[PDB]
Amino acid sequence: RLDLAAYRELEAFAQFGSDLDKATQAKLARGARTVEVLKQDLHQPIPVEKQVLIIYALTRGFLDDIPVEDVRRFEKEFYLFLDQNGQHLLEHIRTTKDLPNEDDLNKAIEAFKKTFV
Amino acid sequence: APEIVGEEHYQVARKVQQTLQRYKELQDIIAILGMDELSDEDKLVVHRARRIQFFLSQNFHVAEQFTGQPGSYVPVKETVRGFKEILEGKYDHLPEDAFRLVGRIEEVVEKAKAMGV
Amino acid sequence: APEIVGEEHYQVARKVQQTLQRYKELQDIIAILGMDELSDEDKLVVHRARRIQFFLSQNFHVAEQFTGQPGSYVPVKETVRGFKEILEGKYDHLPEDAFRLVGRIEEVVEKAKAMGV
Amino acid sequence: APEIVGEEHYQVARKVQQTLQRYKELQDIIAILGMDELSDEDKLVVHRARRIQFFLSQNFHVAEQFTGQPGSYVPVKETVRGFKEILEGKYDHLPEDAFRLVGRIEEVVEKAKAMG
Amino acid sequence: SLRDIKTRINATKKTSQITKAMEMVSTSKLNRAEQNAKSFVPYMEKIQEVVANVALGAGGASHPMLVSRPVKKTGYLVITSDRGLAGAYNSNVLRLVYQTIQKRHACPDEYAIIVIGRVGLSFFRKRNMPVILDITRLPDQPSFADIKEIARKTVGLFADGTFDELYMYYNHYVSAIQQEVTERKLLPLTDLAENKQRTVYEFEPSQEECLDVLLPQYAESLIYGA
Amino acid sequence: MKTIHVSVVTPDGPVYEDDVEMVSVKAKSGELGILPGHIPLVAPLEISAARLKKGGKTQYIAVSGGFLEVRPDKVTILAQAAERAED
């Protein structure tokens, strides 16, 4: 929520990117990616655990290496990777309604990035 | 309603609407600040929005007493083709007035030729 | 319009109304950005419309009891004369304040001289 | 304004309002240029204005269920006193954080002494 | 009507946000520009000291640039911006130049125009003013390396004889609110500030050979300071 | 041994401030060497590098058309562009 609000109040400065300080450039870069990840296709629901995991990936900085045009595809491939080998994380979220262990989560996200292109 | 059009036609139709939405927002900016500041980035949007908007007009068979012309009948394939060309920039060089009150895009090319392009 | 004025006085009256109409068109943009963004020929319109607008005001006999200034009676020929010279540019150098609350066009000259121009 | 406060308390309250208004205008320029350019001249205003803005907060009795703070009741002549001191610069040496979420001015001195 | 008022409100809000961003970024660019001017100061001071010494302290009117000659035509150097939305910044300088050359020139061949920035160039293409040299973007940083060539050309035009006096018209910065139009005579160097101090001066070339390389660089440096 | 402060200045800003013990330039008259206490001397330079010696160690600074201004206590280089060797 914080990132989205800051981006909305910064929108008018985006036209002038070459001139901004690095803090504002960071805020704009985060806002563009947040807006990308909040997109969705009609009639395609997502499970809550997958929603939480992708939002965690966004807000923890893992997604700010990808170009804003790869964010949707990254999300899709990440879901497939989770289906294949993040079953312990998915099960832990389903059962405890809580975030999994941060170190294991970070390892999973970095491992997926090691195979993204 | 995405399916039928969905592969070819839906992508062209939504890209036309996105271009015309941006041009509305630009029109109040455009007047004062905008024609200099927009002239680099956003004039690429405005230059195509002017042409897309002129090409959406047509000459009708029953409107001859109003237009001095006979009418035209455009099949959907040719429509979708022509708008895809204009969005790809194959016609950015032709004058914007050639696009007015024609049928097929070949007719735009012919009218610009007659104008002396 | 038609008869009486129609030759001499009609040309002056229509030139006055045309100038005040164009000033009224510009006033909208003058409000936001001032006179710094006008074209050099559209700046002359403002320059002379201010003079014409101030010269249309007058000092009345009955307003002496508000203000110690005695009023003035101005003939139609002098009225037409004065507005013709202002429209030609004969007094484009005088401060606009010399035109306020006077009778004949000569009083503008004397008032500016009194003001110290 | 007029009667009661109008002699003592209205002079203190008007100085508090003028100081916080000045800081709001400064808040736009402070962000880029003003971090350096305020830092001498306007830091005298900003350093005191942030301490006034923190001292206006308080620990509520009802807040004890959110955080373990007993909460306090501060009389009008004590708040008039404390703000007069801060406006006089008695307490500028204390960190801004010492002024936060506290009762009378003395507890600011105690909080600062406890945090160093 | 109510709908028209709603549309006007939205339009006015959109433009206000854009002018507010354009204000803050100009505020940043002003701060960087002032620092950039202060950066240049030691070199501007050293060359002026040495020039005073060499030309006035040690010698006399032996170089063409120091010597007044009767004026066969004068060149006007005017610095204006490349885009609008500044209040009177360009119109002031253009007005001063136009008025001065109108009041002290009768026929077009008496003068030439060297201009910087699109706005002044257009102001002179309007009318039929004889503009000899131009440049535009000077991407205000112009790394300064880009403006070296326009400066050498103007000095060389004076040198070859096409000018007898050369002037500079530009806005001078006082503060955020006060920018004062300014005219300075760029050549000849008819008035040089004195200082007494000097060090052990060498003579690998002569006085004349020293001047032949010194004076053009001093003029180019005055242009860059303006 | 004796030190002299050397300054390479450009219109963009500074470029080198230090007190090396030698300094070899390529001036109009030819190659020039400078020791501390040198008599005042001004001389133009052409495109070359200025060699600076500190403790035997040598330093190179490229100079694009400068002017040398020598004082017994300080030496100034006024170059229109000048970059260090490693820059």
Image: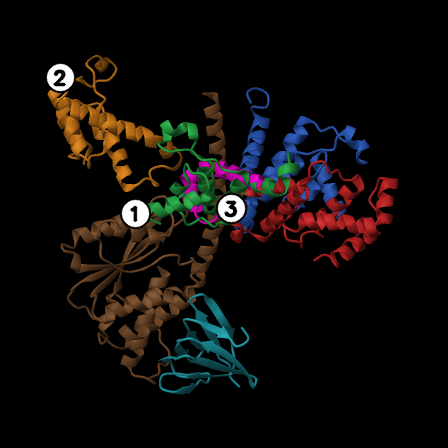
Chain colours: A red, B green, C orange, D blue, E brown, F cyan
Labelled disc at residue E92:
1
Chain at numbered mark 3: B
Image quarter in which the C terminus of chain C is found: top left
Q: Secondary structure at mark 3?
A: helix
Q: Amino acid at mark 1?
A: Asn
Q: Residue drawn 68% across and 44% down?
A: A37
Q: Which SS type dominates the magenta stretch?
A: helix
Which of the two marks, 3 or 2, is nearer to us in this view?
3
Query: Which is more toward the observer, E72 or C60?
Result: E72
Q: Secondary structure at mark 1?
A: helix
- Would residue A45 appear left or right of B33 to someone viewing this image? right
Query: Which is more toward the observer, E1 or E68?
Result: E1
Chain at numbered mark 2: C
Q: Amino acid at mark 2?
A: Ile
Residue at numbered disc 2: C4
Q: Position of residue A34 (x, y in %)?
A: 66, 44
Q: Which quadrant of the structure image shows residue C37?
A: top left
**C117 is within the stretch colored magenta:** no
Query: Which is more toward the observer, C72 or A55?
Result: A55
Magenta residue span: B13-41
Instruction: Categorize mark 1 by other alpha carbons within 10 Å: few (<14), some (14-19), many (20+).
Output: some
Q: Secondary structure at mark 2?
A: loop
Image quarter in which the N terminus of chain C is found: top left
Disc count in the image? 3
